[PDB]
Image (cartoon, chains in turn purple, yellow, brown):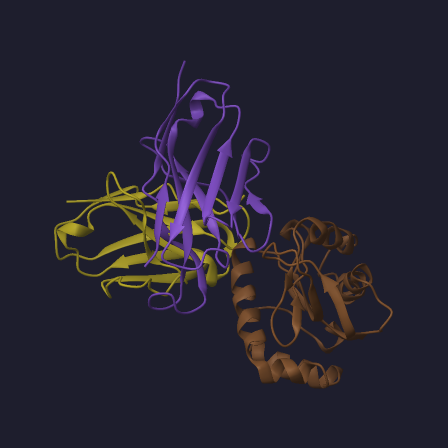
Amino acid sequence: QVQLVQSGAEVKKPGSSVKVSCKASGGTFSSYAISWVRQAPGQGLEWMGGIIPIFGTANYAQKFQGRVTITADKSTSTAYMELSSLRSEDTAVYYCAREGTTGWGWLGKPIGAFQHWGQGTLVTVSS
Amino acid sequence: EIVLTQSPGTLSLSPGERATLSCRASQSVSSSYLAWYQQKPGQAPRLLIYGASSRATGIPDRFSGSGSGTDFTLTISRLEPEDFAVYYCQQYGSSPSTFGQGTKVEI
Amino acid sequence: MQGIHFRRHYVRHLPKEVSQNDIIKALASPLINDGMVVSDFADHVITREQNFPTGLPVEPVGVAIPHTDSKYVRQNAISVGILAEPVNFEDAGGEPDPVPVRVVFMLALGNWFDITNVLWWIMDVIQDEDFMQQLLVMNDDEIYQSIYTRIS
């Protein structure tokens, strides 16, 4: 049982930047990988990157490397995704997703695959 | 990057039937790094399978995954009306994680 | 911890004169030689440790888990180092108090998505108070055999 509560929707102008947050609850925060996955309005899923909060640095997909910044606040159990230089292409629903644990409840090792998902944050880019 | 090509693109089945979905990889992915997802409209993806074969918590035995190397297959044994949705396959054996395009299961 | 490469030549007792940069460079040598990681692997582990520490103030023995970005690793592996006396590492939780580390688990992980699995395994290993206390006295082969069983 884990909840991932994301921030509200964003109406952005082209060229600006957006910071979406993911607030984790119901389990350990620092010991598990938190990923960020995107989905355009009528399209498929797309992995942007992720962060393991006990360790420092985020892992990025080469396409987003340069304008996506993923961080994790240990002191509030909140993960963030900041996408800069917003194009019209970037109009999509942004999910934060946390890996599962191989077992019931809070028990067992991590599985890697994203068992828990946020409600989704819709970002639209238009002048 | 590793491209995942799913097949079929769309599949119309009547309830109670067996749906067989495929996920072809551009390269060999070790069986331990492939997952299957279910996504209904206006919702987040739901994890079905994670170890290519292993089931996520609370997922029925109607869903079953299988495969190795390049070819992987998701099998829904007995289709209920709740099962008709989009299904994705995922590789997380190397960075970055890539998804399939999705197979829409219809009525 | 599936397919993690681990040999007898990945276990070392470092002398009493060493600093943390000496520990990192020491533990990387057997990995670099076998071709598990790039040649400048030690540098990136030292660089990351400064900004993002890996010190775990666990009782009774402090533990370090130094590593770097997965792009610098080719084939997965792990290198264990035992220290003659405490070496100070910065806390990975962000506390100002230092961690007196004696056991170092250098991680060379190629896949980022299985980092949490190796971490979970370490947490389970360092929870066993009896085994951790034995690591301080056992020799290179005795440590290999004990750890190799724990991986399988």
